[PDB]
């Protein structure tokens, strides 16, 4: 087990990029000499196992995290400035998703791939009338939603359970109060346990990323590499313009000087960029918070709230991916479908945990709203090719999310 210990003790982020570049070389070299059936039958199953691993823990982590999160939060009317706090992030998320559509049309990623994994192109199914969709949010059986795999009914049932369980903790009866604590602790244990499994799966990602990239290179060929570069470059330039478009303009109109703003915050983004974990990068956020030389009481609630609420960078990733998959599958997005992208993506960005890899887990939830379920083999193939390239894209989107946190707290502080 000498080599096993060395392999584990290494930056997980570095290995994925090492695994990604190695996979690309192997696929093209093999593809030039043929052996298309060789990779399809020998190295493909490693990629499929990684896909099944991610889908395993999506359901248990959605239910447990919401119950713990909803119970902890209590309605305090947000005082006076809090209503100004929550409204700020909601509007900004809409802008980020809206910018994704125009930039995606500018480059048009996913053209000329022609997925035929299932033997035929994906055929959209007509959506049921909106009355049936809304009435299905309420689960007729709370246990049925979990077992059958429905996600929307589970979210509704999880939220109300957390709200109902925080009243018992405040109840005067001792037996009722004690029973509420035990039930909350058991679910909190399940949510914590699901996070340790996330680290275990990420250690298998370099092997999983290697298998997925190699399989795609051999079949599609060198052509598919070009589009993968287009989506790679698109997100960064879209994020780059977004920072100047909305984050800079608020600084200019108000009295805070943007040039000095980044000078004190320069260490903040750089530390987050290296670690690529916005939720875990909290200590530096409070570090710069206490050395701004201003009030701390505003910082008592803004940073914990803005940890999960603000996720502009991931939001652009969610929107661009949703559009990219449609082009690969050959199904054009109508105007009506584009309207539900921003509504779904913005609320989706709210539920993101913040740890790296969370966007991949909840990207599929937006796909269900569009009408592209994961059970479709054609959708699975296109979605799998994104899972390989997530690490390099996740390097940039963390910086935007943390920057929006730091920028947003300062402008309200000026008021
Ligand atoms: N780690 C990303 C989120 C993600 O990777 O899904 C962020 O905090 O911006
Ligand atoms: Na936002
Ligand atoms: Na979030
Ligand atoms: Na954030």
Image: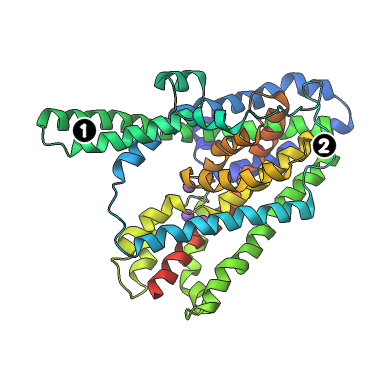
Q: Earlier in the sequence, mark 1 or mark 2?
A: 2
Q: Is residue 119 visible?
A: yes
Query: Is 412 on the left-hand or right-hand side of 105?
Result: left
Q: Residues within 10 Å of mark 1 (few under 14, many from 20)?
A: some
Q: Is residue 151 visible?
A: no
Look at 64% across and 54% down and name the residue there. Answer: 98
Which sits in the foreground, 256 or 35? Answer: 256
Circles 1 and 2, Cβ within 8 Å, touching? The answer is no
> How many numbered discs, if any?
2
Q: What is the C-alpha distance between the residues marked 1 and 2?
A: 53 Å
The residue tagged 1 is: 181
Q: Residues within 10 Å of mark 2 (few under 14, many from 20)?
A: some
User: Element under label 1?
Assistant: helix
**Residue 167 image offset from top left, x and y in percent:** 22, 37
**Residue 164 image offset from top left, x and y in percent:** 28, 34
**Residue 57 image offset from top left, x and y in percent:** 49, 28
Look at 47% across and 43% down and name the residue there. Answer: 351
Query: Is 234 on the left-hand or right-hand side of 285?
Result: right
Look at 78% across and 42% down and name the residue there. Answer: 110
User: Element under label 2?
Assistant: loop
Query: Is 227 on the left-hand or right-hand side of 76?
Result: right
The residue tagged 2 is: 113
Which sits in the foreground, 87 or 308? Answer: 87
Residue 90 in the image: above or below residue 344? below
**Residue 203 image offset from top left, x and y in percent:** 53, 34
Residue 106 in the image: above or below residue 390? below
Question: Can you say which quadrant of the picture contains the C terminus?
Answer: bottom left
Mark 2 C-beta closer than 8 Å to ligand 1? no
Which sits in the foreground, 397 or 17? Answer: 397
Mark 1 C-beta closer than 8 Å to ligand 3? no
Query: Is 198 on the left-hand or right-hand side of 215?
Result: left
* Way the structure is coloured: rainbow
């Amino acid at each position: 087990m000498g080599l096993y210990r060395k392999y584990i003790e290494y930056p997980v982020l570095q290995k994925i990029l090492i695994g990604l570049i190695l996979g690309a070389i192997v696929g093209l070299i093999l593809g030039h000499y043929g052996y298309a059936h060789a990779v399809h039958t020998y190295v493909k199953p490693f990629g499929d196992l990684f896909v099944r691993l991610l889908k395993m823990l999506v359901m248990p982590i959605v239910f447990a995290s919401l119950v713990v999160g909803a119970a902890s939060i209590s309605p305090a009317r947000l005082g006076r400035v809090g209503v100004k706090i929550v409204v700020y992030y909601l509007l900004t998320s809409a802008f980020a998703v809206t910018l994704g559509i125009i930039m995606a049309r500018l480059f048009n990623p996913g053209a000329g791939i022609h997925l035929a994994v299932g033997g035929q192109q994906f055929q959209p199914h007509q959506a049921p009338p909106l009355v049936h969709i809304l009435l299905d949010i309420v689960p007729t059986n709370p246990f049925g939603a979990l077992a059958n795999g429905q996600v929307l009914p589970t979210i509704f049932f999880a939220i109300i359970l957390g709200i109902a369980i925080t009243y018992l903790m405040n109840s005067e009866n001792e037996k009722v109060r004690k029973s509420a604590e035990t039930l909350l602790d058991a679910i909190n244990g399940l949510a914590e346990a699901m996070y340790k499994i996330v680290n275990g799966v990420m250690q298998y990602a370099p092997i999983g990323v290697f298998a997925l990239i190699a399989h795609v290179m051999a079949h599609q060929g060198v052509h598919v590499v070009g589009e993968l570069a287009k989506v790679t470059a698109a997100v960064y330039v879209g994020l780059t313009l977004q920072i100047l478009l909305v984050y800079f303009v608020l600084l200019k109109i108000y009295g805070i000087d943007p040039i000095s703003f980044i000078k004190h915050a320069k260490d903040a983004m750089l530390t987050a960029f290296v670690t690529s974990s916005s939720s875990g990068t909290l200590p530096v956020t409070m570090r710069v918070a206490k050395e701004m030389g201003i009030s701390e009481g505003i910082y008592s609630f803004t940073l914990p709230l803005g940890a999960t609420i603000n996720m502009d960078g991931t939001a652009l990733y969610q929107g661009v991916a949703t559009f990219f998959i449609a082009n690969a599958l050959g199904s054009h997005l109508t105007v009506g479908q584009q309207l539900t992208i921003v509504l779904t993506a913005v609320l989706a960005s709210i539920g993101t945990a913040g740890v790296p890899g969370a966007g991949a887990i909840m990207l599929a939830m937006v796909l269900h709203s569009v009408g592209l379920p994961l059970t479709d083999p054609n959708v699975a193939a296109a979605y799998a090719c994104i899972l390989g390239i997530d690490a390099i894209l996740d390097r940039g989107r963390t910086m935007v999310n943390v920057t929006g946190d730091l920028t947003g707290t300062a402008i309200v502080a000026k008021t």
